[PDB]
Length: 140
Image (cartoon, rainbow, N blue to C red; front, side):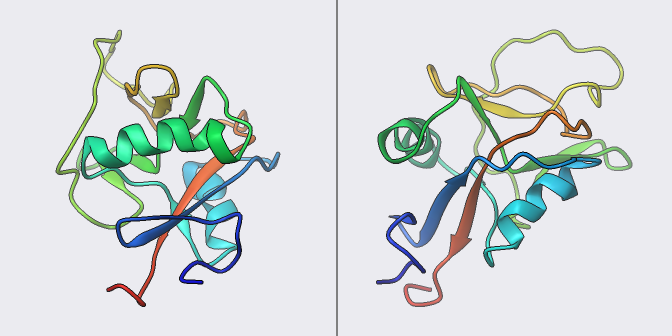
């Protein structure tokens, strides 16, 4: 087992788990805590392979919402969307959305249906589930 438990789905070189945890999310760092609690961090897409993986995988193993939070945060200083994986956003499935100055009002969620993302950061408490991605040093 590369992954901690069987609820962890191994993909390429990482392990994924959805834990629909209802917690007071102050910032996306708070929601991302749900994952860090498991030694993981929020999901991070570097290819459609990941994007479309999560997409089915979510519903295939776990429940599956219409959209899962991406593990992407909006650094308002850089004004960038960043992966909690701490790696460059080298891939993106951005859909055409409405976008004001700040998209801090919204967060980034990958759409379970199509695999499209929304812009933002989850600085809202309305997050009850995040996908966690942790890499496995076993395959690193």
